Image (tube, rainbow, N blue to C red):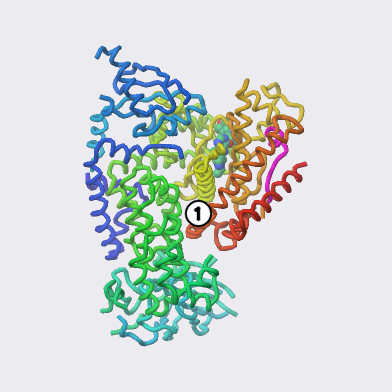
Amino acid sequence: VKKLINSQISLLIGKGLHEFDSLRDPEVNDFRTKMRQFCEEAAAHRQQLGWVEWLQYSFPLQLEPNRALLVNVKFEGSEESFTFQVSTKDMPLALMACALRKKATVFRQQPEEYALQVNGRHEYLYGNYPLCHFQYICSCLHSGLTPHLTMVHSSSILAMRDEQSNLWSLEQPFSIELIEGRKVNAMKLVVQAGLFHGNEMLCKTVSSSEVNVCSEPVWKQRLEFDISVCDLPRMARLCFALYAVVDCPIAWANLMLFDYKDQLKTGERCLYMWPSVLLNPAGTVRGNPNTESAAALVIYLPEVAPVYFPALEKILELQLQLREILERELYEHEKDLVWKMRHEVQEHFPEALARLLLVTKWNKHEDVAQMLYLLCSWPELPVLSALELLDFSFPDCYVGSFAIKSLRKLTDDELFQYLLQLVQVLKYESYLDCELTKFLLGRALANRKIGHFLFWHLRSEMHVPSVALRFGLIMEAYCRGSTHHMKVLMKQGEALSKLKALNDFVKVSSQKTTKPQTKEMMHMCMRQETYMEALSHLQSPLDPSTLLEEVCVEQCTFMDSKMKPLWIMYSSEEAGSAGNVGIIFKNGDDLRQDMLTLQMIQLMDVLWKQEGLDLRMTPYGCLPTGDRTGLIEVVLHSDTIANIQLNKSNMAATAAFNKDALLNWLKSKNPGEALDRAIEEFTLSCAGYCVATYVLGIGDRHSDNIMIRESGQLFHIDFGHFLGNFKRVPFILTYDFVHVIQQGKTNNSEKFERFRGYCERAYTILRRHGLLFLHLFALMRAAGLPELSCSKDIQYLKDSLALGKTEEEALKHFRVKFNEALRESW
Ligand SMILES: CCn1ncc(-c2nc3c(O[C@H]4CCN(C(=O)C5CCOCC5)C4)ncnc3n2C)c1C
């Protein structure tokens, strides 16, 4: 039971719990105890919530950011369904009320006691919301499908809640002694050290002498730094870099001079180094776990006298004219100006806190103590301000603790929109228990959808040693917190476990035998008991509310590309057509870049919708779940503009010229005046994806990676190369699109200038929120993507949105780019 839950978590996280105990570190032991307690208290509250409050945890509503419609309804036990026609503006209780009135006539004799469950889905309909605000209903409007829902009584929800139960005196200069190590390289060796407190150095760099190449070396040199022992800030970071010289990089290593309990670190320390591709402060403050092959370094940290960092009480005891002109990087005369006027910054420019923190001297403990005094009575800044404060440039913990006080006011949906970045910031952390972790973990245990996504965001990075312990430990506390969801997640891992083995079997066979022979062999490998049991009946990792019930083996296949991605189709009896959903399993390519690009498109859709403009965007699911291994959501009822341009023999869209093909495919898929809606659908999405790709700098755009839905909506795929790193992009407007936009006419400036309008409106709304994009991409520098490595990459976004201009200039300049693509298009 306890052993059963323990051996489950080990299988689930992919690391044995004993592997934590083997280290015997009191931090890891303190983390595991302090968290377990926290998450168990979270689970205790969760068990005594109301039935409607449990639905908000387990099935959080899926809402969007007059004209009646057909609706199907039924009850939990029976299969007898009733069909209604009710308003888009009707509340779910008005619908529920009818469902009782129809049973009152057939069955022959209280709405608030029930909830509306979406058939064959982990989605419910409740609350004070008109039915056109739900995703499943709004989906059914556009798509023309019929909502089929089940009436679940309060006691039936409560039956689940029960079954889903578990000091300043040290003025001497700072110094350390570089003793000895052990490595392999072909010259002489040097050991450049250097202190830091974020990206900035606490003092100058101090390189060692030249020892020879043949080495298991010894130095024993007292390296003295240009900073006092009391001047050191609580989050002081000492880095090191080993390299050969006649340059030749070899390895790096870092550590916190203070321990986790606030005490200075003592005498001798062994530091196992990580390999290089000159100095790296961002790199983790934990030794290389490959204790064997990793080159080590023993160093001595002098005995200064027990010295803890001072408590807050001790830290608490210790013209406005040309001020604004600069406040909108800065010179030293300006930096001094900003530090001098720090009180009026709190009292009349609180949102400038970040620019003020960067001017303070962290290598002089007076300026630090004076800054921390202001921060204790600084007002709550908005969410965008707090996001700026979570970057690597503000390592101080009182800042971090403040940013979390500000972030606490995030909506469960905004948290989900930012969660990816919040996880990459966990890499920057110095100690295991922290606010961010405690916060994420608490939000995760109050929302099963956050719990789900946070879990896969951690699990997908376990193959990386820099974070294996950190994440493994976090996932463990989540599993202590949600013992029922843990089991739900194990079924997904085991599905993914089989999907891996199936894809290797698919990779070999496809080389040897032909495609159809590999296909019937894939189907046979699938028909087995283990595969049918493992790949069936599970919540989708791409979306916890979608249920991947029965696998339709006949339809499952694999795309003919390189990594042979598996196409896996499903179907549900209960959900009907809403259960017929597919997934794509890729193996051997990292999908974290695709996930970020899709997050950015999903944000752009949300920003535009929030300013009344729906461009009919398609931010389909993409989810890394392991080492070069994730899931992509099959977008159904769509084809590539390459397959449509094949102009296939005796089809419903036989066209004479390529330019007409696109439009002819639309005419066949949408008969009557449905075509007018499909062209309107095409036009907005076309305008949408033109702006998103321009801004995100997505290149290598060809007919085989631009799709189009049967509804008319245009959408892009393969987001492996962005920010103009093919693996400065121009604006794109293919002639075949301009034809469909212009209703198939050579001249239609009425419909074209409308389209141009959408591209301009969308471009500006993004520019307004250019900081949000900057602050989210700023935190992702922690991930370690090849194309989001440095400031030069971020710069692409600054220059694409032109944040260093006015709305006149930016739109004046953007109007030229559009014309330059319009002209280039034949
Ligand atoms: C990161 C890569 N990425 N991102 C989005 C995607 C991706 N490719 C998709 C696709 O591609 C078509 C293109 C060829 N094809 C087939 O031949 C099918 C024929 C019938 O049996 C099933 C296969 C499927 N169709 C639908 N959704 C897709 N998605 C999300 C991909 C692959």
- Does residue 626 appear in this view? yes
Q: Residue at x 27, y 29 (%)?
A: 112
Give me the residue at 59% from left, 49% from top. Answer: 764
- Residue 6: give x, y in percent of width and height: 27, 49
Which residue corresponds to the image point at 63% horizontal and 20% vertical from the top-left?
A: 672
Q: Nearer the viewer, residue 558 or 743?
A: 743
Locate residue 169 relative to residue 790 in the image: left or right. left
Q: Quadrant of residue 178?
A: bottom left
Side (left or right) of 83 relative to 38 = right
Q: Which residues are magenta?
A: 730-741
**Residue 184 visible in the current orientation:** no
In the image, ligand 1 is in what quadrant?
Answer: top right
758 w.r.t. 647: above or below: below
Residue 345 or 601: which is nearer the viewer? 345
Q: Does the stretch in magenta take in 259?
A: no
Q: Position of residue 751 (x, y in %)?
A: 68, 34
What type is the residue that disc 1 sits on? Leu
What is the x, y in percent for residue 31? Answer: 28, 60
Left or right: residue 568 versus residue 440 is right
Q: Is residue 757 left or right of residue 372?
A: right
Q: How many marks?
A: 1
Q: Which of the image's four quarters has the C terminus?
A: top right
Image quadrant holding the N terminus, namely top left
Q: Secondary structure at mark 1?
A: helix
472 or 596: nearer the viewer = 596
> Residue 136 falls in which quadrant of the image?
top left
The residue to which callout 1 is attached is: 772
Q: Position of residue 271 (x, y in %)?
A: 40, 72
Q: Residue at x 33, y 67 (%)?
A: 376
